[PDB]
């Protein structure tokens, strides 16, 4: 659904604390600026891609305590309140099966993992 | 029908708790971004035809007018390394969007309703589907007759 | 450079600004001191000879 | 000096295999649980290396080349092998190197040393106070330009027959005037020519001498209780390096544990 | 240590914060590099001690504001940094200054990150 | 449905079997390996 | 911008100090020619996908 | 002929398979070329 949100300081990556490099870099124009627009535009899409999928409901619905569904056991997909993150067994198995300085920073997502499980 | 449903649920835990290549679609997304970032950092050690990769070593060895020529080579190479990275991520961001618009379409047609579309909400006659979250993605459990 | 609100207007090139969030600059910690370390410089030659 | 030793006999050009021997740290950089490559001079694995032996009528110490660096695996029961000659002409005509272990320190000198027909480390007068120490290497030295002494240690030259227990591996190359050495020390059970295993060789020194070298030769310890000299019992191997691409597996503590030849 | 400074070692230079470490260097190893061939440690030449090279803090600066028509009050976000320079609240996105924190929950008007949002109200 | 597969060695296209030109290309970085990954990833998609 | 488009014509005619300046011009032109090709194929393949 | 070899045909350096030409030619022709402006053939200076 989404990718990792990233941003790159085009000046810091090329000119690593070198004012001589910066003065030369200014003669190339807005090449520095255009790159931050594209990555910023990518980052906004990863938040819309999550809203388009999970935020399909206008109000939150809760599971009742008396879980009588005619013999159907939804325990493995329903959230386990005993956990710190209110996720299901299957939601936990999927998370376990999956695994700097040069102007390179990683932005976090808008919706945290707990919010996704609520939807 | 209830025993058949509960038994099929148990087989999923046996598969996901043992098989590693089941979630290859999501792992390839994580690995793709990591290689692009590491490749972007490794190109800083490249000279691009200069005496060295480090600016201070060029500044602490050569004169200004001789260094400004060689510094222009690192800038030309390092600047292309960004365009190669940003242009790739723009394409990777299109494949992920089409996959996201699909998942949004399946959450509406498969989960929020019953679909008569074949092989869209699972193999066989679709009854209902249950979603499950995951890192950078989503999982659909398609019940079929 | 008067205030961050003005840094936005110079970034967008518009005296008017709409609601939202706008990236304007890149904060960076400037270093304070300058360390120089080198091994001990002993083993000099006896030039007095 | 000029007289050939009584125990001089020409051995044939033997050959044997090398499982993974000839792997060293190409730089002083630390790593931790990674797998990085490199492009430097190494030994190709499972290659043909020459074999040489010694015994109290077959004294083996010929001249050999130094085209692109070499490798040593000096099997030693008694530290018979002492030092190594280097240079181009190996005589007083031009500068040359010597690396002599006098059983107390690694004495190193760079002079236009005078060449003998069969240099050796003479250990004479074993009738009283043997001491297995230094006592026909050369006869003149002029225009010395370098010297070096190492940490203090003690080696012994007492005779011991049978099969080997200890092995000392060394590496020698000269790049851009800098003469580099890598080595270690480890025990073995010399059941065959060499062991099928792996162990990395650490750096020892780095001398900025700044000469050309094209040949070398070994130095051995002779006892006597030039003709009248008792030959020793030892064996040493020789290799030659090539610019091959390798992989290096560094553990958590930074010690290399395995490698691959690309 | 614990200060953003420049480095000029015997055969190495750079910039960053320097701290002690538990890494086990060999007696002949001088510095270390990471997977990306970037320095992250160094052995002091005058004292056999291993020291980690943490990079100096950096991050993008973004402002939180409603429209100019509404008002000119503005808050500021420092992405990916704890509060160092100094009405201030730390988040997983960064040190936020110029905005008040509330235990109540509302609808998102101005996204920030990590579940946080902002809006101009009473 | 599919497209014609292609594979292009960066070296032979640029350096026509020249050791000098090749050694000058190593200092340009991993630009060659990235191009081979992309074309190979395209060819695999045509089979899927 | 080089003297010739051939590589061997420069390799057999000029010296390395004088040829290195010329070969670098061919690489910068021939390297961009690949990036323009690979970038366009990735976009064409997205339509086929 | 019929072998990958280096050659210098009066300065026409290159490397490839030399074999007999079953193609026409002008009297004043000295060599041929392909669509890629690459040396596709050659006349020997001693035996035309």
Image (spheres, coloured by chain):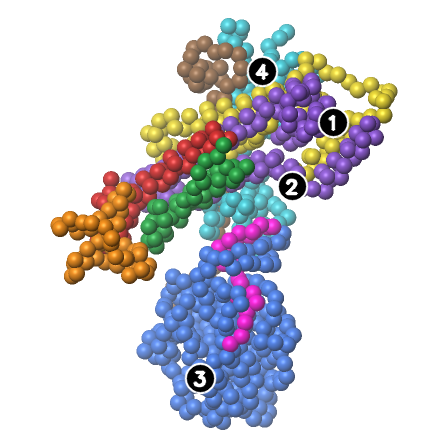
Chain colours: A yellow, B purple, C brown, D blue, E cyan, F green, G red, H orange
Say if labels 3 and 4 share a chain: no
Residue A119 pos. (x, y %): 69, 21
Residue B39 pos. (x, y %): 48, 41
Q: Secondary structure at mark 1?
A: loop
Up-down relation of residue D196 to residue E57 (above or below): below
The residue most toward the left is H28
Crowding near the residue tagged with mark 2, few <14, some 14–19, many ≥20 C-alpha atoms within 10 Å:
few
Say if labels 1 and 3 share a chain: no
Residue at the (46%, 24%) spot, across then down: A37
Quadrant in which the N terminus of chain E is drawn:
top right
Q: Quadrant of residue H44?
A: bottom left
Q: Secondary structure at mark 3?
A: loop
Q: CA distance from mark 2 to mark 3?
A: 66 Å
Nearest to viewer (mark 3 / mark 4): 4
Residue D174 is one of the magenta-drawn residues: no
Q: Secondary structure at mark 2?
A: helix
The region drawn magenta spans D15-38
Say if labels 4 and 2 share a chain: no
User: To which residue does mark 2 refer?
Assistant: B21
Query: Which label was assigned to residue E110?
Result: 4
User: To which residue does mark 3 refer?
Assistant: D119
User: To which residue does mark 1 refer?
Assistant: B145
Query: Which label was assigned to residue B86?
Result: none
Up-down relation of residue C17 to residue A113 (above or below): above
Residue at the (38%, 63%) spot, across then down: D177
Count of marks overlaid on the render: 4
Quadrant in which the C terminus of chain E is drawn:
top right
Nearest to viewer (mark 1 / mark 2): 1
Residue at the (42%, 79%) spot, across then down: D63
- Is label 3 in contact with label 4 (beta carbons under 8 Å)? no
Give the chain letter at badge 1. B
Q: CA distance from mark 1 to mark 3?
A: 93 Å
């Amino acid at each position: 659904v989404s990718m990792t949100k990233t941003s790159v300081d085009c000046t810091m990556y090329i000119c690593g604390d070198s004012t001589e490099c910066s003065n030369l870099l200014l003669q190339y124009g807005s090449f520095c600026t255009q790159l931050n627009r594209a990555l910023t535009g990518i980052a906004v899409e990863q938040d819309k891609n999550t809203q388009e999928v999970f935020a399909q409901v206008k109000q939150i619905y809760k599971t009742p305590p008396i879980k009588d569904f005619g013999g159907f056991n939804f325990s493995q997909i329903l959230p386990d309140p005993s956990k710190p993150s209110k996720r299901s067994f299957i939601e936990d198995l999927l998370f376990n099966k999956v695994t700097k300085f040069n102007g390179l920073t990683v932005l976090p997502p808008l919706l945290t993992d707990e919010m996704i499980a609520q939807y | 029908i209830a025993n058949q449903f509960n038994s099929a649920i148990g087989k999923i835990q046996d598969s996901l708790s043992s098989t590693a290549s089941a979630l290859g679609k999501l792992q390839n997304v994580v690995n793709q971004n990591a290689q692009a970032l590491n490749t972007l950092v490794k190109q800083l050690s490249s000279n691009f035809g200069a005496i060295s990769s480090v600016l201070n070593d060029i500044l602490s060895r050569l004169d200004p007018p001789e260094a400004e020529v060689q510094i222009d080579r690192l800038i030309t190479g390092r600047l292309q390394s960004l365009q190669t990275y940003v242009t790739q991520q723009l394409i990777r961001a299109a494949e992920i969007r089409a996959s996201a618009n699909l998942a949004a379409t399946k959450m509406s047609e498969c989960v929020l309703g019953q679909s008569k579309r074949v092989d869209f909400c699972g193999k066989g006659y679709h009854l209902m589907s249950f979603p499950q979250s995951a890192p950078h993605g989503v999982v659909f459990l398609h019940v079929t007759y | 450079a008067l205030d961050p609100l003005s840094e936005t207007k110079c970034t967008l090139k518009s005296f008017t600004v709409e609601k939202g969030i706008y990236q304007t600059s890149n904060f960076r910690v400037q270093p304070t001191e300058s360390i120089v370390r080198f091994p001990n410089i002993t083993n000099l030659c006896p030039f007095g000879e | 000096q000029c007289v050939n030793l009584r125990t001089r006999t020409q051995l044939p050009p033997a050959y044997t295999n090398s499982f993974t021997r000839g792997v060293y740290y190409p730089d002083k950089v630390f790593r931790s649980s990674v797998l990085h490559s490199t492009q430097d001079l190494f030994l190709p694995f499972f290659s043909n290396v020459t074999w040489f032996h010694a015994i109290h009528k077959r004294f083996d110490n010929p001249v050999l080349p130094f085209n692109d660096g070499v490798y040593f695996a000096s099997t030693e029961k008694s530290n018979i092998i002492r030092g190594w000659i280097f240079g181009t002409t190996l005589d007083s005509k031009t500068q040359s190197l010597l690396i002599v272990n006098n059983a107390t320190n690694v004495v190193i000198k760079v002079c236009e040393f005078q060449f003998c027909n069969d240099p050796f480390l003479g250990v004479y007068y074993h009738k009283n106070n043997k001491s297995w120490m230094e006592s026909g290497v050369y006869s003149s030295a002029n225009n010395c330009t370098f010297e070096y002494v190492s940490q203090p240690f003690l080696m012994d030259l007492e005779g011991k027959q049978g099969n080997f227990k200890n092995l000392r591996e060394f590496v020698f190359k000269n790049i851009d005037g800098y003469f580099k050495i890598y080595s270690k020390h480890t025990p073995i059970n010399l059941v065959r020519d060499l062991p099928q295993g792996f162990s990395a060789l650490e750096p020892l020194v780095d001398l900025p001498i700044g000469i050309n070298i094209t040949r070398f030769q070994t130095l051995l310890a002779l006892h006597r209780s030039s003709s009248g000299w008792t030959a020793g019992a030892a064996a040493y191997y020789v290799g030659y390096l090539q610019p091959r691409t390798f992989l290096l597996k560094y553990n958590e503590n930074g010690t290399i544990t395995d490698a691959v030849d690309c | 240590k614990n200060k953003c400074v420049n480095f000029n070692f015997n055969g190495l230079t750079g910039t960053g914060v320097l701290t002690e470490s538990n890494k086990k260097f060999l007696p002949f190893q001088q510095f270390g590099r990471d997977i990306a061939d970037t320095t992250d440690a160094v052995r002091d030449p005058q004292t056999l001690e291993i020291l980690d090279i943490t990079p100096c803090s950096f991050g993008g600066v973004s402002v939180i504001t409603p429209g100019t028509n509404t008002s000119n009050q503005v808050a500021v976000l420092y992405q990916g940094v704890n509060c160092t320079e100094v009405n201030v609240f730390q988040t997983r996105a960064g040190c936020l200054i110029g905005a008040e924190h509330v235990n109540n929950s509302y609808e998102c008007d101005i996204p920030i990150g990590a579940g946080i949002c902002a809006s101009y109200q009473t």
